[PDB]
Image: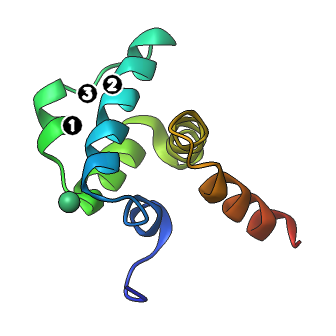
Amino acid sequence: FFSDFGLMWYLEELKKEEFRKFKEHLKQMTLQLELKQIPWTEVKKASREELANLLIKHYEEQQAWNITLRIFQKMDRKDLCMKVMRERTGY
Ligand SMILES: [Cl-]
């Protein structure tokens, strides 16, 4: 999908189960590092575009990305982390 941008495009790099696991990691971590929480029901049901917007709405843009990239590295989606980094760097 060359139609999509930003965080949403990355969440679309995740398959069905990965996305499902992504949401479980997100909720764990937000709890672990003690941020204001999103209701687990909202998180669980969210589409990729909706979750991307939930993240940015609750944590603003930079933190939504940093949180998302931490989860990727944790889920063994290190390719996504390096991809974003090669881009943001100019490599
Ligand atoms: Cl899906």
Which label lies toward us, 2 or 3? 2
Which residue, given by chain and number where applicable, does mark 1 sit on?
43
Residue at the spot 46% in from the left edge and 10% down from the top edge? 32
Residues marked 2 and 3 touching at CB (< 8 Å):
yes
Q: Earlier in the sequence, mark 2 or mark 3?
A: 2
The amino acid type of the residue labelled 3 equals Ile
Quadrant of the image where one finds ligand 1: bottom left
Disc 1 to disc 2, C-alpha distance: 8 Å
Is the residue marked by circle 3 packed among few (<14), some (14-19), or many (20+) residues within 10 Å?
some
Residue 49 quadrant: bottom left
Quadrant containing the C terminus is bottom right
Which residue, given by chain and number where applicable, does mark 2 sit on?
27
Q: Earlier in the sequence, mark 1 or mark 2?
A: 2
Left or right placement of residue 37 versus residue 43 in this view: right
Quadrant containing the N terminus is bottom left
Callout 1: SS: helix
- Which of the labelled discs sits on residue 38, or is there none? 3
Residue 71 vs residue 16, the one in the foreground: 16
Residues marked 1 and 2 touching at CB (< 8 Å):
yes
Residue 21 point in image, percent of width and height:
32, 37
Residue 90 quadrant: bottom right
The amino acid type of the residue labelled 2 equals Lys
The amino acid type of the residue labelled 1 equals Val
